[PDB]
Each structure stands twice: as structure tokens, then as C-alpha cells.
Amino acid sequence: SMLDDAKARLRKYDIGGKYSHLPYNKYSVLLPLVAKEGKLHLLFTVRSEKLRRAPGEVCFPGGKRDPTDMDDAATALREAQEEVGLRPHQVEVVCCLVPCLIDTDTLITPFVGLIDHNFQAQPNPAEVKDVFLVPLAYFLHPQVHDQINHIFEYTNPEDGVTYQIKGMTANLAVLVAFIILEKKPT
Ligand SMILES: COc1cc(C(=O)O)cc(OC)c1OC
């Protein structure tokens, strides 16, 4: 099926705990996959205007590891719960993708998780201004604007609201789309 085929594909790019012990400042992100109307979607947040780093920007749920976390996946789940209400029984963590190195001293580890069909986002307004879905297929033929560097513009046909997606967030979305959608019979 669609979901089982997505997980089998994702498991082949799983690096595991390989890079997890290295002595970095550590952050984790969740890439949440949602099935709606026969198709896979990614869930995104718009950061609150009040935040210190990157107010008003599109990003995945995530943040900094703390001493309670058993592992890097636990960081991602804890942060997703606190930002958009996502509970642990509502997410299956499928795999750990290649981490991102930033600023010489920081490592960001992304996890892909399948989200239960009955989940509804309760955004925390102190951290999250907005939550939205994008069809996974969009990342194969995006609408690109050059800022000189590449920015994606997505218009939700439900309400005509346009979002800008860029940087690490845009790169990870394209990656996940390639992994799951490349080479499929129609
Ligand atoms: C996981 O949080 C981050 C995300 C990004 C980003 O590029 O989206 C940049 C960061 O630092 C420069 C972050 O914290 C270190």
C-alpha cells in the first residue's frame, strides 16, 4: 500500500545512531508525513513573530536537546508535542536521515514520522503562528523565485494563502519527495 511503500523506501536511507554521540550543540527536527485524499503531505509550521531566531519563517517542528531526552528522536517528539499538540501515540518514527552541520559547532538530526489520520494541530501561539500541509509531489515541480539563491512559493488552494519555504527546510522536503516518489508506476 501507499504507507507501507513509503516506509520501506525511507528505511533504505536510515543512517541510525552513527553520528549521534559526536560532541556538538544538538538539535532535532520532525518531518511529519500525513495522508489526505489519497496522497502524502508534509506538515510545516510558521514561527511566531515573538521568537529570538527566525521569527515568521517556515520550518519543521523541532528544537534543542535537553537532559531529559533519552535520544535524538525523543527531542523531536517532545518539541512536536509542545509546539503543535502531537502526542507520541500519534507518531511512528520511521527513520533518521542525514544530519545537517551548521556554524562549525552545531548538528541538526532530522527524523521522518508517519502521523495518525485523526490528528489535528493545536498550535501553541507563544511559538507557532500557523500550521499548514503541502502535497509531497509539489517538491518535484515547485514554483521557484530567485532572491542570488532559490526560494519556493506555495499557494494553498483551500484559502489562497501563499507561503515561502527556503534553506534547510526546503532542502529536506525535496529529499523526502525524491526518496518516496522517484520511479513509481502510475
Ligand atoms: C534546529 O534549529 C535550527 C534550524 C535552522 C535552519 O536553518 O532552519 C538553523 C539553526 O541555527 C542556525 C537552528 O538552530 C541551530
Image (cartoon, rainbow, N blue to C red):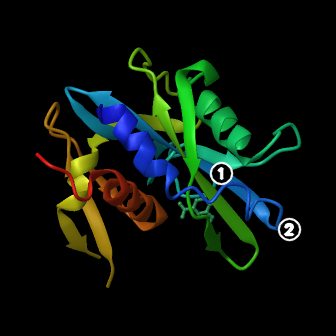
Residue position marked by numbered label 1 in the rendering:
28
Residue 174, relative to residue 42: is it above or below?
Answer: below
Residue 162 visible from this viewpoint:
yes
Q: Position of residue 48 (x, y in %)?
A: 51, 42
Quadrant of the picture in which ligand 1 is shown: bottom right
CB at mark 1 closer than 8 A to ligand 1? Answer: yes
Marking on residue 23:
2
Q: Which residue is located at x 32 percent, y 54 percent? A: 177
Q: Where, quadrant-wise, is the C terminus in this rendering?
A: top left
- Badge 2: few (under 14), some or many (20 or more) residues near its Cα, within 10 Å? few
Q: Position of residue 29 (x, y in %)?
A: 59, 49
Q: Which residue is located at x 75 percent, y 58 percent? A: 26
Task: Determine whether, in the image, residue 31 is placed left or right of residue 35.
Answer: right
Numbered label tally: 2
Q: Which residue is located at x 44 percent, y 19 percent? A: 119
Q: Where, quadrant-wise, is the N terminus in this rendering?
A: top left
Q: Position of residue 18 (x, y in %)?
A: 73, 62
Residue 183, relative to residue 137: is it above or below?
Answer: below
Element carrying mark 1 = strand
